[PDB]
Length: 49
Length: 51
Image (cartoon, rainbow over all chains, first blue to last red; front, side):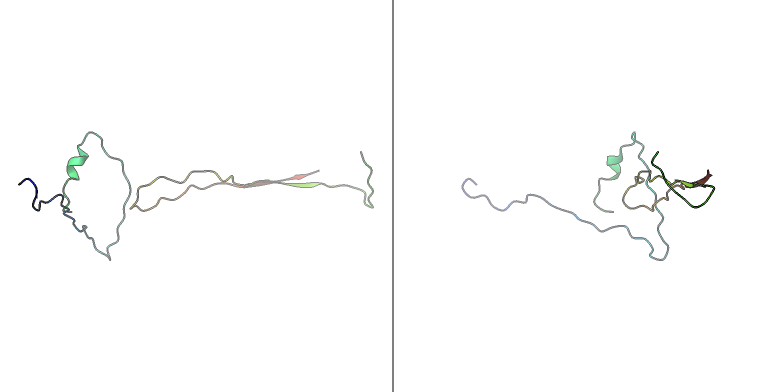
């Protein structure tokens, strides 16, 4: 109440795994620049992959 | 003209000019997690000279 405060959570991490692909299929990737008008932060919110 | 001596008649100077390919170019910029892209082709030249 006043002199003793009980247990109370502070923070929380929800950590996830990645998105897999095929080993034998072979990745081919190239870097492109963003389109700035799109809200790119909206796409990257959730921790689940 | 400091003097010099030889035993033969005619004097041939053969100059070999060399324009090596100059080490130019910057490394290409990319993002981590990408397949690389190759470099351009450069040229070296050799010319000679007779006197």
